[PDB]
Image: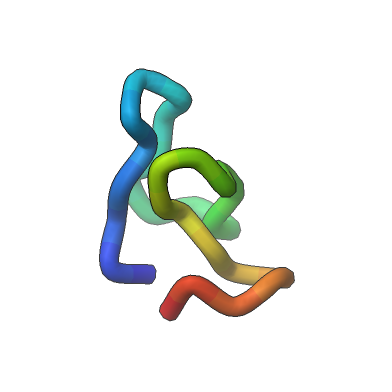
Length: 29
């Protein structure tokens, strides 16, 4: 949950992303 996106998105919620960053259900932090 350190954020990220690289133009993908992000911002709390349930995580998401991948990029570029993100995380949640898949880690990231």
